[PDB]
Length: 307
Ligand SMILES: [Fe+3]
Image (cartoon, rainbow, N blue to C red; front, side):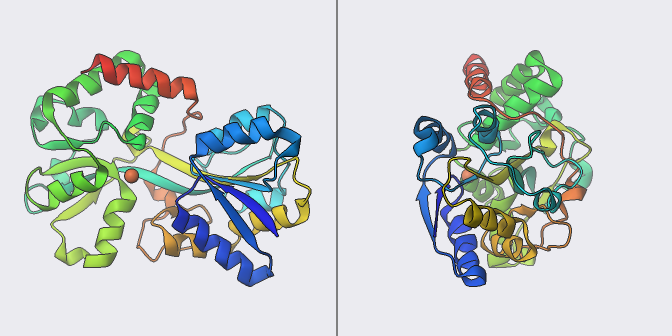
């Protein structure tokens, strides 16, 4: 049996954990929490951690753990299973990316068309979109979007984008609420994450929704994908079962279990989502460095300056 520190959504974790128990017979105990908090705990615990595996919603939390010498190497065959072009790779082959979540523009297709959409996420924060664009400034993915803009286009562009949304956007408390506002005719478009919409579409049927998705693609900052993954702790005294779990997560069966539970993009090339997501390759996600805690602190500062 293994202990898994779980930073991912409990339905994702529970699903893969139950599918693992059926394929192998090995029990999984989850210890859930925020990815950043669990990473801190793993570092404090060090060589006396009870964790066998860290299953995290954000691969960025691995960087610090890897540099602290706290992660075990993973099989090269296992890493290769999800190593599509664009997918973040551990320089020391000591963690693996497993699935992705995408930024997207949702729009009311009875009021706007794909031809009305913009080639960059930058362009939505302009007077053309007053007040026709929803955004969610408190959302974690929104913060990640700001960090990506700062890294890819520089700080002045990121701040200008935020100031543009202040001037031209409609603020919503949550992504779910922004999606409702679009469906309800309150705002014709919004910046959200993909999974909210794909879940609604699976549940209601796409034909019964006013809204559709527009993906900016071509490695625009607004094509940002955030990655979930896993690592084995070097301190684990159950390496064999911990590695078996991570191997399972990268396997066809492990990926099928994940995509049935959550509308995330599988990173295997041979797995299709029952939510009817596009292949990961078609997203044309940018390549960006891991978000550090320092990156997030800085993005919050920019959100503050913008009002
Ligand atoms: Fe959310």
